[PDB]
Image (cartoon, rainbow, N blue to C red; front, side):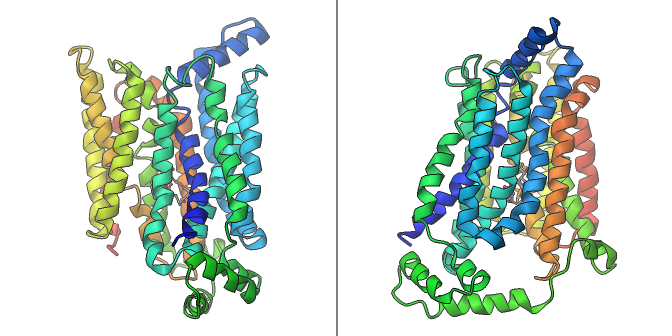
Length: 447
Ligand SMILES: C=C1[C@@H](C)[C@H]2[C@H](Cc3ccccc3)NC(=O)[C@]23OC(=O)/C=C/[C@H](O)CCC[C@@H](C)C/C=C/[C@H]3[C@@H]1O
């Protein structure tokens, strides 16, 4: 419990860095867009086209999700081959590579570097979100396993907040220091590169994946702190039974078996309902949507959304263990729909009532607050509770693919939709939120 605080906190750095890379490109949108325009002129002696500037900066934020897909797929590769700890350590290379790329992108007069860096760091984020939850789950005692695993969640939302803070004009969200805003991630990396080597390899890797039972003994005693461990050791060997009991099934075997075709449908749709709700429409373009509203100091409203977001995350902890998954997920979609509607009213009546800009802030706060209690965590609780230890692994990969894919559809196309639909964009979210509300009220069983 003492030395334990090192290995965990050392791993959560990746989840901080995960959330940081997610929301850094929110506030400094205009300045980087100005840099694209600046770079476009220097090359061709011509101001960039507005539609091109759209899909270009959209690609710069969207390509990140593409990396995450690949990353989340490759987690199984490095984990069982190089170990949990060492996997997290070596993959800090992607951060330094990406940090340098996104940092010297301005000094290199190239948005390709920035896009490329955004891809690479996306892979790291996809890999990391597979490492951290798995590492702490094996390192922590079973008692604190259902509590320390929270730090991954908190890490992301807090990382998103810090990204939005630094996104201020006062700090790093400006003409001169935006390349550093993207690069500062090297600090967390450098820290994790120092800490992890002192942290212990997971015993479940030493006991199972290496059969080095003896090398695992020295871990738990220093790790768990307890002198003896002739019960935690037997535990893992008894929990590995259930994990090795029924045969694990592959991805494409999940599609072909009509026994698995119904629960998988629920899983994927529940992931679509998380992204196509359009919470990344705000976590990527909060400061942008606020600008089209009459919001004074919009970057602060984004930080507001971060704090509200971070807040209701902690609230959700003391709710999932108090209510049902079917209910909480329904509550979310409704509130997200209501707020999406309420958002449209603000964006519509602003031109008539020069103050509804304040309503848009409250709407989006509720739009993300209702998300973090319903469609936030639940879509990952239902999937893990619709499949036994055999097909459950393959189900996460599909769900993971479903999430990244639908995440890319929003972040890449939301601006193209924002131009044509005008103040009537959140209706798309409202509409889909209804379909997702119908789909769950009938076809989603409580667990
Ligand atoms: C906006 C988002 C962010 C906010 C989350 C979103 C909400 C959430 C928050 C806390 C716990 C579980 C879910 N639900 C997510 O899953 C979330 O990433 C995670 O936080 C955890 C991801 C796990 O590693 C498994 C999936 C890891 C990836 C395959 C998918 C990651 C999704 C992101 C999502 O983009």
